[PDB]
Image (tube, coloured by chain):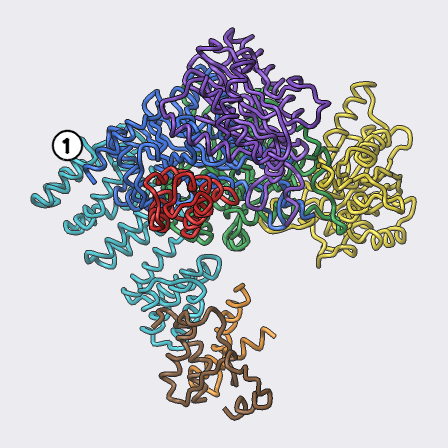
């Protein structure tokens, strides 16, 4: 027949859920954002699109942190991931409440993928319109994960989502080749900044703001934290030079 | 959304009808013809085993005539399965009623009991009704022998005699023709058998094609005695009709 | 010895070595020996799979019984083997019993010992429960009678076999009884009859698949 | 469709015969080259060629390439 | 030469080959053809020693709607 | 009406297309995987495909260790894989907890199959479009192979494969097994058995495989585990020798 | 989430029909032809073990399954549906009967109980009827041997013998031909072999075929000794050997 | 109608028997041959 898409849990005649696939639509539409696992740790980079001067700088913050070691960022409908994020914040809490440890990134990774996939399991459950790049330093190093409304996430040497991901995925692939060694968080900070501007070239039509956060076994000790001030401004001009 | 999938069972016809109820009734037309009669001295129960065969085992088989109590047994027009549900329930209900009052249930109470139960699906739940209607044969203190009926709608009446399943109008005609108030069971027996043989859609009316029972206060009695006839007994009385 | 292979194999060897008759001391012992379990299906020893394998001898050993004429031994034992596959499986009887006797129809036998034992086990069907293709045996018995040229015996049996096979018993067999019956008629030179029977068969034969032999016949 | 091998096979066949650097990224493209056909492989070349004429390349450079590759892996698989 | 068609082989034979000597005017082969099915014909047509005529419904497609059946008769 | 397509209810033909469509999402990930009982052991070989550098390849697996003893490989959407594995993982411990001993492999499959069977019958539940493959060395059964479908249907296997070309691999082994007449590989060392399979994997796929190319897992007595790329390559070494 | 299909999924046709059931019957008819025969001394059921691949190990799939030492079941239809019903059937038997009465229910009630389930599927929302019908044979003390046939209608009735699945019509045809009252199981066993042979297309043998009986109690199978009252299960499953043994007896 | 087929086969027999003279026996076969078909599909 037809209209298989018209209800979530339905399998398409080819066995697919177009709703999720449609949810994927706005995901791309979601603000381009990336993440990087550097040598010790991970870095989370996202463009903050400036809609207007009435927006107050730095105030509306995209990247969200789970526990204290896990940052998360997503292209898509903000309230979605937020809603999800809270659940993750719940998850780790329960996890840590039970396990006394902060949660391993992959552990944390898994739990969500279920909860997302749960929203693939019912025609009444609206899949998620977001894909979160997320991770942090954990017991064993860091990890870099981006979870799809499909309920699929993976380990990522680098990760990107939203519009400009291609420009990103380009640059990420490069740095992989530029630095199969690894990367210093600092350069991880710096390079992402360039990538973002480059990624912004798709959305170049409007001005934006740049938000980048990171989790460094070294620099944040394994905490997850924002890039701020000079170091933030550094990568900016570092990129703002390199963009030219 | 779930809405797509609801047949919306209980919704009214624009004419204020319930087609499921209508259609349930319709399947009952397809149900094996079942007849019952309240004689002066008793109540007769005869129904056609429908869809029969050689290796079909008759003796244990009862697909139609079931005993709720020793003062209440019933003939079933409809899905064998569905009734057995209600059959069991009513028994309990009666048993409860018995266990409540240490006294047998006046039949209608049990009847009306099932009546609204059917009606339960009628007015709520989005649940298909039962495709079953019943001949309610019972003896009470109050009215003595009582011959009731029910429809999936739960609407129900008393009868001096009644038929259900196929050929009802035909039977009803024959019944409403040949019946007379003072008829003795054995008359009604053959009378039904007469009506049966005639209203029989198959060639011959034969025991192996029939279920038969009676409610009678015996000659040595004070215990109004229900009896289901054995195939031979049916076959025997089958001869006594001259039907042979 | 003592082993399902060994003795049987010895009984097989002592044939391969020399003969069944030496091997019979093992063969007889096969029946006399080898198992701790199940039923006494061996006529002496109590066994299950062994007897089946003792039969494996008793097949050969039967044609060796024949090669002895201890078919005459086995003749009477053929009743016992019946009870012995009754000590195992009544159907397995019907297989092996028939098998054996047919193998005694092989390795040339007097019609008698066949008839004699057939007629035995034919009844030994009934005595057990079996109305069931004792006629098949009886067919052969009739065939024996046919080979005995007892067509009276045959046809009389046959007509029963017929009335049996007339859908009181098998149509596929009912095909073949005609064939024998036809031959019977044919040896009696009753042509239409033989024809009819063959014809009825042949037409009825088309309803199923028939033995290529039968088909060829 | 050609396997990752078959692709890489066809890759260095259809593609590399267009003038290209060794800088031009041979397997990693193939790595990102998945569910392509023989002409899709050519598209991969042809697409980078856009970037080539966009980067002024007779020899395709890895720059031209994997932009295309994803871009090739973009529209469909 | 497609093995085992006897009943069908006899059937055609029953259908045509025999009545050619001695009743149907026409016979229908049904199934996938050229499977041996069409091969039935030629094989039959071979033995038959009569003037064979193959025809294709897929042949009568000439604009000249004037001729059409004309030899379809005379053929 | 035509919603029967959309939901799980008998077609006019008595069919569940959501199920049959879920059978699509099975090979959707396009991984040809296999499982063979070795002599003492059982080995699963599968395609490990990495489309992207930016991925972590190591994070990519459809072979999941359900228990100490039981590993499982999945064919279908990774989320359902990530979903189903946990479900299984929940069972064994609880089975182990409830029943004092680790769940024998089939039981899991039998258990898991029910869920699909539930999803099969339940409407609001969609089934999962993954086919599951359960092997381990069962203390009672030694090597054992069990594969479940979205239908809740499953069976034991002398050996089995899964994927788009599963059909051919099936043939190859059938031929081989008919040739061998034996249900399991005679090879004692799964090492060989791995190489054996990879051979027949390479064979029936006509495709050579590098260390990254393959996802591999090893069912051993009391333990399931998965090989490294080295172990893979190690096997890849010797196969290059025999072949 | 939160199943909002609470509404009966199968609804009475304008013609007063339940299509899913009908389609279940359709699917049931599609089922592998499977039979049962109630003889004098007992009852036998039979079906062809279906191999969708020789790599698969047939025995690992059991279409016949004991419900009680005197009761076992078989189906024609979707294996999985049959699978879960077995457990419930097994369970409800213990719970609703044994865990009450300390024993194994008379064939009818369990059957009556089982069918109850299948009905529920037909009626309650969110669920579809099962893709099988059931040939169920059991011996009880009072009703002795009995053989039942349950549909997705949840309807059930006894048989002298019967078959379900595809060739069942042809089977039942030949069954009626063959069947008599006085058939002893072994002949009936043999009969079933004959009968199912027709429904059998590919290889016919104990490895292709699944046979079991309701027989006399089997103290060996009782797994222990010392209890006079319990002489063991009447049910048993038949070995390919025993099968192929009697397939010689064909 | 089925009767006709019987007759035809009787002749078909007889024709195959090379007979414009049909016995009863032929019919008696066609019965089956038709009741073959009658029992067939």
Residue at the limit of the structure toward the bottom, as seen here: E74
Chain C color in figure: cyan
Chain in green (letter) = G
In the rendered view, tell whether residue A24 sits above or below residue B240.
above
Disc 1, SS: loop
Q: Which residue is mark 1?
A: C1
- Chain given the colour blue: F
In the displayed structure, would residue E33 be above or below residue B75? below
Residue C136 % position (x, y): 36, 56
The residue at the far top in this view is: A100
Relative horizontal placement of residue B205, taking residue G129 as reference (left or right): right
Find chain H in the image and tell me its colour. Answer: orange
Chain letter matching colour red: D
Chain E representation colour: brown
Q: Drawn colour of chain B? A: yellow
At a point 63% along the width and 50% down the height, the residue shown is A1
């Amino acid at each position: 027949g037809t209209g298989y898409d018209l209800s979530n849990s339905v399998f398409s005649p080819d066995g697919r859920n177009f709703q999720v696939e449609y949810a994927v639509k706005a995901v791309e539409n979601g603000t381009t954002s990336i993440g990087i696992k550097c040598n010790d740790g991970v870095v989370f980079a996202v463009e903050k699109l400036i809609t207007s001067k009435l927006l107050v700088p730095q105030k509306n913050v995209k990247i969200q942190v789970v526990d204290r070691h896990i940052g998360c960022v997503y292209s898509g409908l903000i309230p979605d991931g937020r809603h999800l994020v809270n659940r993750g914040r719940e998850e780790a809490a329960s996890f840590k409440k039970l396990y006394k440890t902060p949660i391993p990134i992959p552990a944390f990774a898994d739990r969500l993928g279920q909860y997302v996939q749960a929203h693939t399991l019912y025609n009444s459950v609206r899949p998620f319109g977001v894909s979160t790049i997320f991770g942090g330093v954990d017991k064993n190093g860091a990890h870099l994960y981006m979870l799809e409304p499909s309920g699929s996430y993976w380990g990522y040497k680098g990760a990107a989502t939203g519009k400009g991901r291609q420009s990103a995925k380009a640059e990420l692939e490069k740095l992989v080749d530029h630095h199969p060694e690894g990367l210093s968080a600092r350069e991880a900070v710096k390079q992402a900044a360039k990538i973002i501007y480059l990624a912004h070239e798709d959305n170049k039509e409007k001005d934006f703001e740049l938000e980048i956060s990171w989790c460094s076994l070294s620099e944040t000790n394994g905490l997850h934290k924002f890039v701020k001030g000079d170091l933030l401004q550094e990568a900016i001009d570092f990129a703002q030079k390199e963009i030219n | 959304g779930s809405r797509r999938y609801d047949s919306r069972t209980t919704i009214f016809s624009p004419e204020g009808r319930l087609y499921q109820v209508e259609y349930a009734l319709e399947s009952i037309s397809h149900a094996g013809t079942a007849i019952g009669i309240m004689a002066s001295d008793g109540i007769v129960l005869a129904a056609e085993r429908k869809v029969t065969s050689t290796l079909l085992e008759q003796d244990t088989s009862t697909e139609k005539l079931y005993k709720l109590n020793d003062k209440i047994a019933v003939a079933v027009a409809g899905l064998t399965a569905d009734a057995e549900i209600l059959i069991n329930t009513a028994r309990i209900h009666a048993q409860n009623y018995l266990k409540t009052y240490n006294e047998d249930i006046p039949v209608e109470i049990l009847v009306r009991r099932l009546s609204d139960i059917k009606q339960g699906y009628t007015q709520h739940g989005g649940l298909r009704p039962f495709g079953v209607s019943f001949i309610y044969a019972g003896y009470d203190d109050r009215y003595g022998y009582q011959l009731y009926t029910s429809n999936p709608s739960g609407n129900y009446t008393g009868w001096k005699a009644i038929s259900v399943g196929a050929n009802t109008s035909a039977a009803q005609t024959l019944l409403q023709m040949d019946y007379k108030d003072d008829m003795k069971v054995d008359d009604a027996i053959e009378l039904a058998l007469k009506t049966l043989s005639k209203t029989t859609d198959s060639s011959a009316l034969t025991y192996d094609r029939l279920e038969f029972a009676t409610i009678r206060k015996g000659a040595n009695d004070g215990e109004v005695y229900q009896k289901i006839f054995k195939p031979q007994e049916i076959k025997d009385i089958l001869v006594k009709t001259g039907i042979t | 010895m003592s082993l399902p292979g060994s003795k049987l194999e010895e009984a097989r060897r002592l044939v391969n070595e020399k003969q069944y008759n030496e091997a019979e001391q093992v063969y007889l012992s096969l029946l006399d020996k080898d198992s701790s379990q199940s039923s006494a299906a061996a006529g002496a020893s109590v066994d299950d799979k062994r007897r089946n394998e003792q039969e494996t001898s008793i097949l050969e050993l039967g044609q060796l019984y024949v090669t002895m004429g201890a078919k005459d031994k086995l003749r009477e034992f053929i009743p016992h083997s019946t009870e012995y596959m009754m000590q195992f499986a009544k159907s397995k009887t019907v297989k092996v019993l028939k098998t054996l006797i047919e193998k005694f129809e092989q390795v040339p036998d007097s019609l008698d010992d066949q008839i004699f034992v057939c007629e035995k086990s034919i009844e030994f069907a009934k005595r057990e429960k079996r109305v069931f293709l004792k006629h098949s045996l009886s067919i052969k018995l009739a065939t024996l009678h046919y080979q005995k040229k007892q067509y009276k015996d045959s046809l009389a049996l046959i007509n029963d076999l017929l009335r049996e096979f007339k859908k009181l018993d098998d149509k596929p067999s009912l095909v073949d009884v005609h064939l024998l019956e036809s031959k019977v008629y044919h040896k009696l030179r009753n042509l239409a009859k033989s024809k009819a029977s063959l014809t009825a068969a042949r037409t009825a034969a088309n309803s199923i698949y028939c033995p290529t032999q039968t088909v060829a016949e | 469709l050609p396997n990752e091998a078959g692709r890489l096979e066809i890759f260095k066949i259809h593609t590399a015969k267009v003038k290209k650097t060794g800088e031009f990224d041979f397997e990693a493209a193939v790595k990102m080259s998945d569910g392509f056909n023989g002409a899709d492989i050519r598209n991969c070349a042809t697409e980078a060629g856009f970037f080539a004429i966009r980067d002024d390349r007779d020899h395709i450079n890895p720059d031209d390439l994997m932009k295309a590759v994803r871009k090739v892996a973009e529209v469909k698989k | 030469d497609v093995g085992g068609l006897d009943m069908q082989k006899q059937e055609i034979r029953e259908a045509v080959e025999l009545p050619l000597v001695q009743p149907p005017r026409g016979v229908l082969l049904y199934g996938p053809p050229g499977t041996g099915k069409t091969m039935l014909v030629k094989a039959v047509a071979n033995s038959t020693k009569a003037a064979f005529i193959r025809v294709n419904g897929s042949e009568f497609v000439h604009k000249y709607l004037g001729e059409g059946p004309r030899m379809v008769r005379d053929v | 009406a035509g919603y029967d397509r959309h939901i799980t209810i008998f077609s006019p033909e008595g069919r569940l297309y959501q199920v049959e469509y879920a059978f699509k999402a099975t090979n959707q990930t396009n991984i040809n995987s296999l499982a063979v009982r070795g002599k003492d052991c059982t080995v699963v070989i599968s395609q490990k495909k990495v489309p992207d550098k930016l991925l972590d390849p190591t994070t990519v697996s459809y072979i999941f260790c359900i228990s100490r003893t039981i590993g499982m490989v999945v064919n279908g959407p990774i989320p359902d894989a990530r979903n189903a594995a946990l479900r299984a993982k929940a069972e064994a411990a609880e089975f182990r907890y409830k029943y004092g001993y680790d769940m024998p492999c089939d039981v899991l499959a039998k258990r898991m199959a029910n869920l699909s069977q539930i999803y099969t019958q339940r409407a609001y539940m969609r089934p999962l479009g993954v086919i599951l493959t359960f092997v381990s060395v069962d203390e009672e059964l030694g090597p054992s192979i069990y594969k479940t479908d979205p239908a809740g249907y499953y069976v034991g296997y002398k050996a089995t494969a899964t994927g788009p070309k599963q059909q051919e691999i099936t043939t190859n082994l059938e031929n081989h097994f008919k040739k061998s007449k034996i249900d399991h590989i005679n090879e004692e060392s799964w090492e060989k058995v791995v190489e054996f399979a990879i051979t027949h994997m390479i064979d029936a796929l006509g495709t050579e495989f590098s260390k990254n190319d393959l996802e591999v897992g090893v069912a051993t007595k009391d333990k399931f585990f998965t090989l490294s790329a080295e172990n893979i390559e190690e096997r890849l070494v010797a196969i290059a020798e025999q072949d | 989430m939160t199943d909002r299909y609470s509404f009966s999924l199968t609804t009475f046709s304008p013609s007063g029909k339940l299509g899913q059931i009908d389609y279940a019957l359709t699917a049931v008819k599609q089922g592998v032809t499977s039979l049962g025969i109630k003889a004098t001394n007992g009852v036998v059921i039979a079906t062809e073990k279906k191999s969708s691949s020789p790599l698969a190990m047939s025995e690992t799939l059991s279409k016949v399954s004991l419900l009680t030492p005197d009761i076992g079941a078989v189906y024609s239809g979707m294996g999985p549906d049959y699978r879960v019903l077995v457990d419930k059937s097994r369970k409800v038997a213990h719970t609703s009967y044994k865990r009450i009465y300390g024993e194994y229910p008379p064939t009818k009630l369990l059957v009556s109980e089982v069918a109850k389930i299948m009905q529920e599927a037909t009626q309650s929302g969110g669920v579809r009827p099962f893709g099988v019908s059931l040939l169920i044979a059991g011996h009880d003390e009072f009703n002795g041997f009995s053989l039942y046939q349950v549909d997705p209608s949840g309807s059930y009735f006894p048989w002298k013998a019967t078959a379900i699945g595809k060739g069942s019509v042809a089977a039942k045809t030949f069954l009626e031909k063959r069947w008599n009252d006085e058939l002893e199981l072994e002949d009936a066993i043999h009969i079933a072999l004959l009968t199912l042979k027709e429904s059998v297309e590919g290889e016919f043998n104990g490895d292709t075929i699944e046979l079991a009986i309701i027989g006399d109690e089997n103290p060996d199978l009782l797994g222990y000794t010392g209890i006079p009252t319990d002489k063991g299960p009447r049910f048993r499953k038949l070995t390919s050997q025993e099968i192929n043994d009697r397939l010689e007896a064909l | 109608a089925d009767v006709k087929g019987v007759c035809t086969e009787a002749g078909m027999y007889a024709l195959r028997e090379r007979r414009i003279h049909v016995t009863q026996e032929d019919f008696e076969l066609a019965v089956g041959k038709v009741m073959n078909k009658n029992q067939e599909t």
